[PDB]
Every structure is written in C-alpha cells, then in structure tokens.
Length: 254
Ligand SMILES: C[C@H](CCO)N(C)C(=O)CCCN1c2ccccc2N(Cc2ccc(C(O)(C(F)(F)F)C(F)(F)F)cc2)S1(=O)=O
Ligand code: NA
Image 1 (cartoon, rainbow, N blue to C red):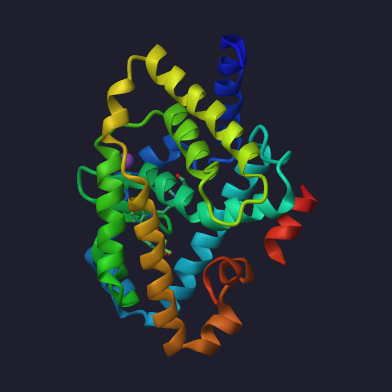
Image 2: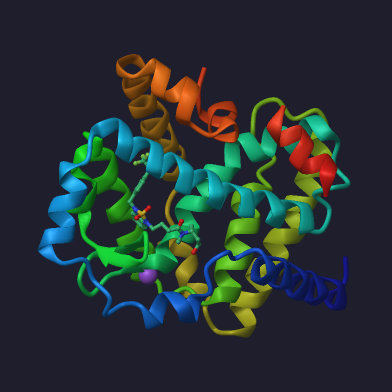
C-alpha cells in the first residue's frame, strides 16, 4: 500500500467511528456539571444487586451493538470470513467498549456519565464487584491522561478489534494484513500530528485482556447467585458474549 492509500484508510476509519460513536463527545462534555446528588447516589446504593447487574448489562449490551456496527463499517472487516468476524467481535467488542468508555469519564472529579448524570465509583456499590469497578475507573483515568482526540480513539479502537493473535482465526494471514494496514494508518496519523509520544504510554494488551477476564469472572459469580435473573432478564447478546445466534444475525442483517 502507498501513502495516498494509507491516508484514505485514516479518513475511512475516522468516519466509521464518528457514525458509530453512540454518544457525541460534545454531549458528554456539556453534561459534566450535571452530577447526582447524595440522595440520588444513596438511591443507587439501595437498589438490589440483581437490579443493578441487569441495568448495567443492558447498558453494556447497547454499547456493544454500536461496536458491532463500527466493525461492519470498518474497511476489510466484512471481507473476512464469518468465523473470523465472530471470533474478533467475541474477543474484542468488550475491549473496544472499555476504551470508548474514557470519553464519558471526567478525570477532574473521577465521575462517569451513567443514566443521565455524572457519578463517582460509589454509585455502583450494589453490584458487589468493587475491585472490577475500581480497575475500570483506573483504566479510564489512565486513558484520560493521554488526551485522546476522536480521530486517535477511532484508529486505536480499530486496532483493538483487528487483532490477528486472537485464538480461533481461520485466515490468520488475512487478518495480519488488515492489522498491518491499520497500524500504518495509526502511526502515520500520529507522526503527521506530532503525537507519536503516546505510543509508549498506551496500555499493554494484557491489560485489556485482564479487565475482560475480571468481567467474566464477576458475571459467573452473579449468575451463580441469580441464575433465573440472567436467564429471564439479561439481554441475549450479552449472554452469548459473556455467559457459559445474535452476533450472526447482526452481521448478516446489515
Ligand atoms: C463506551 C460508551 C460510548 C463511547 O463513548 N460509553 C461512554 C458508555 O457506555 C458510558 C459508560 C460510562 N461508564 C464508565 C466509564 C468509565 C469507567 C467506569 C464507568 N462505569 C461504571 C461501570 C458500570 C458497569 C460496568 C459493567 O457493566 C461492565 F461489564 F462494563 F464491567 C459491570 F459492572 F457489569 F461489570 C462496569 C463499569 S459506567 O458508568 O458504565
Ligand atoms: Na476522559
């Protein structure tokens, strides 16, 4: 691939992300003063564990649906075989969400945009997974220190998804070629914008993998306590990705 092709890939990736970003960045910023009162925080802490898990699983499922659309609009993704499309989304969708979440994180007060207002870590105490929540808040805090532009988030999350090392890929070489083109696009954009210094500050890949593992572990603990809640009230796309059909139809329906 030549230079003009790399720059066209940069614009293509940034456009696909803008169309699928779900929450507009300026909308997230304009709401930073809108914070839950102590009474509203107490209301969240008084909710039952299973109610809070269901609500968070619903919110996560909705965000994942936008990551699926990002993948479908991503250059070269729909060219891969269906097995590899599903392998990449199963391993990478949650990792993309984890990176995207930093846009709704306010590092000044350590609050996140959740259900219409900003609140701190204590909002989620009823989940009974404080270590996982604290890890996600720290991860978003680390990403916030990099001051990602929207274009940088686009290119970085494309690479999080297009990972040729995922186990189960049938056409590993094809994914390797697409990953390399995306890496050139990412690094070309950082060089042109004088932002190559962020490369050494990006999180290790085992970090994203560690957070997803924690998520699956806490889910299996909750599912053991409330199996009927998961069966009856968790989104089916959520169960397909994280518990132990939907992705196929999302990819086919376009
Ligand atoms: C990615 C998407 C659009 C891109 O801009 N976006 C901004 C959002 O969806 C908003 C999420 C904002 N939140 C956030 C951002 C930073 C750090 C923490 C948090 N939240 C706490 C939280 C809740 C729930 C969970 C869980 O659901 C999971 F699965 F994600 F870990 C769990 F509790 F079940 F574990 C894990 C942390 S949060 O309130 O969900
Ligand atoms: Na941020």
